[PDB]
Image (spheres, coloured by chain):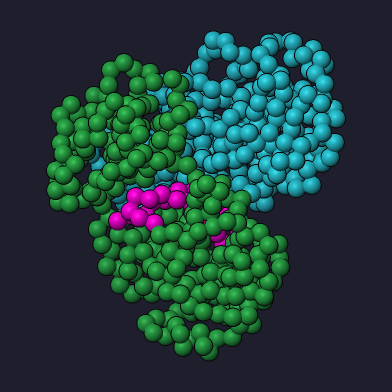
Chain colours: A green, B cyan
Amino acid sequence: SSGFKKLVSPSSAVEKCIVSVSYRGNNLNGLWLGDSIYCPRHVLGKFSGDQWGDVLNLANNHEFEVVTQNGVTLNVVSRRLKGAVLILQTAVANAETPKYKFVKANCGDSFTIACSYGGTVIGLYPVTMRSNGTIRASFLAGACGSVGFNIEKGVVNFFYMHHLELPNALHTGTDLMGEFYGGYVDEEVAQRVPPDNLVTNNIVAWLYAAIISVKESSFSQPKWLESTTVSIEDYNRWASDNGFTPFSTSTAITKLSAITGVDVCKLLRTIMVKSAQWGSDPILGQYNFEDELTPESVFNQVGGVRL
Amino acid sequence: SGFKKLVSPSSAVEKCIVSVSYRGNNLNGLWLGDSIYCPRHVLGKFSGDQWGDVLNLANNHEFEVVTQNGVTLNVVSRRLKGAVLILQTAVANAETPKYKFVKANCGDSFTIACSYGGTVIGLYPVTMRSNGTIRASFLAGACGSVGFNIEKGVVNFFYMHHLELPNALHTGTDLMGEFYGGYVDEEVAQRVPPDNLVTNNIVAWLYAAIISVSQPKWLESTTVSIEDYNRWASDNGFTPFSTSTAITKLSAITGVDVCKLLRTIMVKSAQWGSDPILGQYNFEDELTPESVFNQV
């Protein structure tokens, strides 16, 4: 095991914003910021297609039961839909809304999931936005509405809101503008589950981690680190045909290429070599690629290494 | 997997983390009731028997304690408890959550409030290893950072950072002041015993696999004795198995016996093969049985 962890953001500023939203026997989590509550529209019931708007018109404000964790019932005074997200307006604002921002997550981007049940955050864990717009989480009945976020420069960044479980340990949701990741629908129908490639830039960061942690107690470089390079332009051609995302320039990647000495390309060739066939000498104890440790996460933890 | 290594939420804990500065020295503290718990070495480097004499020379006003809100807390009395220093604040922390101090056992996992200057900048899970150490993040958070979890509405505080070892290893005490693994707060040579793989956690991980799916391509159909397995354990770098309520329950969710799993470990241990378990070719020993049961 390494000293390079998949860090989670502290949840103080988010917990204050999570509430439960109930509508005619349906229950899930909502996100309270200002005088707006964001939650998945299916709290309205098992609908589909163009039914939502009609259902909303027929639904009534007072039928939406919203309760804070402190046991306070909030009154709803207006309702609307943005994409697959229902935004309920509260009579009074959340006095402790933090500085926040709705951002769209890319492939590889990592963030924290506030696993919630009944409006209460019961746990946290990191996840990465896969290539097929899904994420690998640990949700249970009622987890719907849980948000994905991180904290950067004192601003809460909301990237995700959980909507449903696509069979087999997979889940999907929207950003906070209401746009589903990928293009899956909040329905119980088809699961055209697209390609989930292994993120290349996270492998690079992870390899830079193994190298760094190995150098701390050895003189010799890892027995799996190739000496021959390959081109950025070249790796991609191989990636698309083998299930790997396209390598992209990253300041974080740069930062620690200049610190370890190794070059990204020696690492890329390593990916090819070990992908085609993994030897019998593990990287950080593993005989399989680590896909969710990001360049930024590795760089931020490197400082703690004994010089 | 859709079993994950869970981290506990931190709001309640963040309201109790503070900044404790002394004479040049600086680190984190835990404020509960009207007490602040922090490592005693904030006093400086001392040994054996001198901590007590050193404390008596200190002026409570030399202890600068600041909350995350920037409020300065006035220290009114002090004491030592094991390797932990405890300061009394003029006022009680009116936002003290229900809590309990518990000693973590080998294999227990909890969350580290990665803190610097009294601020939690991140969170990460760790597990208590057989030798009394925990593999933290290279960015482990300053001394005083606490390890905890939440169970049935109560915050359980198990650990506090005291000293760093190479390879991101750390150790410290419980909140009663007792060191894990018998280490001491001295920058001196100390023996660091073996870090064995946690059997009980491996077992829970396997069940998570069975459930992630018939009887699997590597599930082994043969059985081993418990005392037989522990026999082979003490000389292969493994922890002695000790069944619990959580384990017993996963064994009921699957028909799979616990001994068939103990077998699968022995086999895969000396020679794994090319049959992956949860897309992995190595053991995951940090996913506890309670955590797996809770995720089903």
Q: Residue at x 45, y 68 (%)?
A: A177
Q: Does the rendering let one see residue B227?
A: no
Compared with B204, B194 (above or below) is above
Q: Residue at x 26, y 46 (%)?
A: A248
Residue B24 horizontal side relative to residue B267, left or right: right
SS majority, magenta = strand
Report x, y in % for residue A121: 58, 56
Report x, y in % for residue A28: 54, 68
Report x, y in % for residue B241: 48, 33
Q: Residue at x 81, y 15 (%)?
A: B57
Q: Does the rendering let one see residue A44?
A: yes
Instruction: Say whether residue A265 is magenta.
Output: no
Q: Quadrant of residue B81?
A: top right
Report x, y in % for residue B95: 75, 48
Q: Nearer the viewer, residue A298 or A35?
A: A35
Compared with B285, B193 (above or below) is above
Report the span colored magenta.
Answer: A105-131
Residue B62 horizontal side relative to residue B249, left or right: right
Q: Quadrant of residue A18?
A: bottom right
Compared with A119, B292 (above or below) is above
Q: How many marks?
A: 0
Q: Residue at x 30, y 56 (%)?
A: A131
Q: Quadrant of residue A279?
A: top left
